Image 1 (cartoon, rainbow, N blue to C red):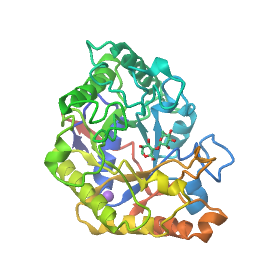
Image 2 (cartoon, rainbow, N blue to C red; image 1 turned 45 degrees about the vertical axis):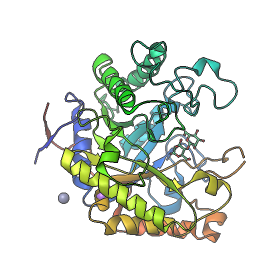
Image 3 (tube, helix red, strand yellow; image 1 turned 90 degrees about the vertical axis):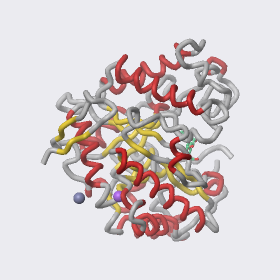
Length: 377
Ligand SMILES: OC[C@H]1O[C@@H](O[C@H]2[C@H](O)[C@H](O)[C@@H](O)O[C@@H]2CO)[C@@H](O)[C@@H](O)[C@@H]1O
Ligand code: NA
Ligand SMILES: [Zn+2]
């Protein structure tokens, strides 16, 4: 049966429309597991060509949702090209999402001392990057490259590969140049809308669903989520990102569930897909060598028990850095099939999460892209 969909891009390809329809249905039957750099970064992988993952080595299947970033698309592509690996993920029926760690359009010529000129350069650049602003051409250059990438991202039959494109995330904090100290809510909304319009209307991107993802709220209300929300005309996917303590984390887990419940209820009301677009133990705790060997079991237990939170389409955890990060300190979220994670109980935790009937990995999702749809618009 053909389902009626209303997308940000009413001219989206049939496969893109199908992806939306798939998640609309699937989300009330499972939660898909997502992983950033699934087949491009791992502690246990010997090839980064898109054929291996730490997830696969841990549980025998890939993540259902594959996350990557504009750090692999926009010059200087610090994270490396991902076209081949995206194509491999799509060929095995996976779902692709790309987040936007854009450089700072006001300061990107000044790179040298980290974090100058990067997403993490907190110099406000929202006002300055909108049309009329001096750095609008710099932002447009980034968007040009995203569009060229999207417009040429084709499968073996020459059809465009759908991507869930997540823009200006974690915007309710101030660690990024598009954050809440860097912009009024109206200015942020304009940046998001301008960028979607540029991609869709100026550059003709037809294979994107658009995702919005602030941080978790501690005062979990619709009014709070709506303050910087770009609007129903501009967003297909309602998400949030949340990172918590490794220890004494019951309150944080309740907050995860509350935020997921909110986005799920909002998504049903607004005809959107609710997701958790980024979730994990906070990086500093992992980097200190700490672990919670019940983390994944607590996550799935809490989510599936709640009648609203359970309705999210996916949750995504962050990258498994093969050599960690400079402190080298560990920086990974999927427990690896190796002595350290066997011994500390985290591998068992993740294997139990995989075994859970409500989690969906890559072999658990079928006919994602061939569903008939009608479009409103
Ligand atoms: O891959 C881009 C950088 O990602 C960082 O990880 C952050 C991420 O920026 C988000 O804030 C959220 O997902 O939390 C993640 C973990 O703290 C780090 O992995 C950097 O090393 C990357 O360059
Ligand atoms: Na679900
Ligand atoms: Zn159903």
